[PDB]
Length: 258
Ligand SMILES: [Zn+2]
Image (cartoon, rainbow, N blue to C red):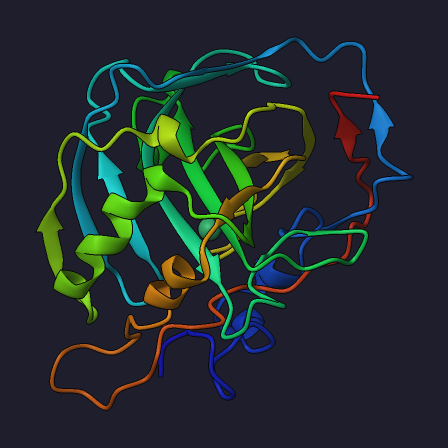
């Protein structure tokens, strides 16, 4: 009876196995744009993905991950609110059963159709496993998806999903350029938070881009054909794999823009 997104194992149940679910810096949160504070101390955000090396795409049950070779400084995030260098390890998405929901962060309570998370770890901690045990261990770039025009750079991801329909399946996925998933503007909000899936560790500097990317109805429809279950198990569509907004508590959200 492990955690998931269903009626009896979903987000309101997670605290029983993971008490930090009710902690002081949990994610996601609602971003109240009018209460967010423009911060002049914020240095420019640096996304250097030119030598990114994707390896594989995997259905882990709760989402699919595109994983990268993070054994060298090849795809890094720096600047913004960050001190030091954070290395890209994987990206994944959260999405809804309907276009009206799916994102984890919300903006003035608005839910987007999906949310992309590019996960990076602080190189001063040597690897991801050690990084998640640190309060500044990860930097996650969050990007909202709305339904409209297709995102051409997403299409290679959507076309391989038929090969990883069920939990446990993986496929080779080399030479994918995550620059094709970024919006024009790097304007962002930032705040200290957590992983949004168990173990919910409070190790994340969140950087959430203001500008969503547009993806087509057909593209998100393909996300919804995935399965939470493994092959040969009862079919349950991988939809609504999002945690809702958590209390902001003693935190301020900062904006990079005015
Ligand atoms: Zn995520």
